[PDB]
Image (cartoon, rainbow over all chains, first blue to last red; front, side):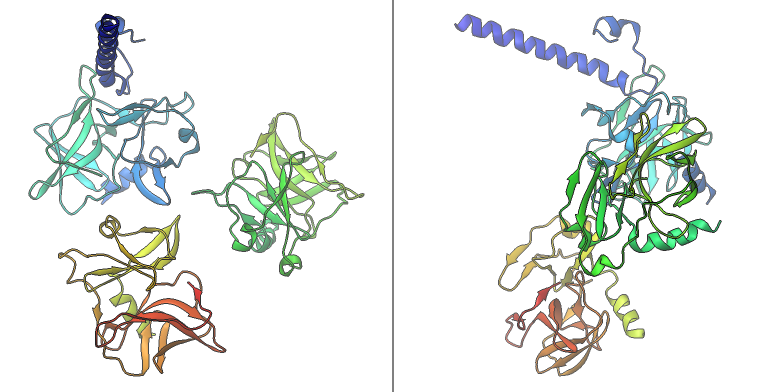
Length: 48
Length: 163
Length: 163
Length: 163
């Protein structure tokens, strides 16, 4: 029970930080009126 | 004199106010097929087309953005990233761009004039006014702008008051 | 010209616009001692006397309709069952009546054009506009009207727009 | 003639209306470092400074009061308790003070003109208009005033209607 709770908290927190970093990557690039995404930050953050 | 008339001629149809029980508290911006609108200004869009949409949020940059349809993308503002230092046109006259900072002389500035874009001598939007802070005699602006790379940079001085 | 001015003189007294938050969405008509209001138009009637009256609804004919107070009964429009072909009047110029179809030359008729009573060559209401469609170079309308028996008749062309 | 101009010159900056979806229903009063505002008038304060406060209530005396800050206490109305009988200045002309009762001639008086202070020939507030009752030809007022001891006396005739 405690190992499943530790693993659950760790996976949920890592997924939360991943979504936080994806938002932090794509927030400056979407507010621009040109609406383009560069080559590296498109595929690595699933931006399309 | 004629600068305010040019601002009223350029921002006539493209600028829509935000109503809140009859009070004008902010102004949206239609540029690049995008509808910029701040967080702290809350109310209904005076335009009927722009009100029936869904705006994606960005609380860190302080911007809500949406997708303007294709039948209105030609009637938008212009935008650019190439800006020198000096003078620019604003709705209440002139604004100085010094050391990468927008400064407005005092006397003007209250609650309600948030979202007015900053124009140049050609007719392109270089910044969007979001807030202001009183600095001695000459106030500074907390705005957003772009760059050559394509990253929306939000400039915010110390202890600003939201308008 | 000349026709629209007496219609403005009539509409200044008895045709009442509705009050959406900043604009006008539709027009309540007071005819024969029975207040009429379209359904898709939502807002508040300008008179505090006509606002408090609860309306009965008729979804087949797209009109709320309540009874007018006794003082207001003499100051109502008049209604006519008999309409011959030709030209009738309207707030936006003239309207053609041909084969039982109120049609209008295009360029006019948009949102906020609802409940405007089509008058006649005497000053009596023959129809109430609820919307229309652009039939090529000339738009037709979707009105309710009356006949010889006393039966409210609604006509609506194909794919009309609720104005 | 000139009395209404003197009322508009004295009550220009110190009188703020109360807005309710664009409707003017009442007027507050800034006197003695206090902000008087009635109960039945509900809405938002047009001034930005006076709206962001907390008003202590008194339902028996029909008054909400607050504390005006020190940077605005010099720009208030004046107040006194020494009043003789006769005539006084009001926003719609003159008002008679007879037997300790304020009377206004008919023709004027509707819903919305609540909270207007009564001035004298010197420029001091002697009463605050809260309600009125129609008495024959000459209406009476239901107001508040002060005395020599310092007790706020609320005068209310029979069967008044709140404005």
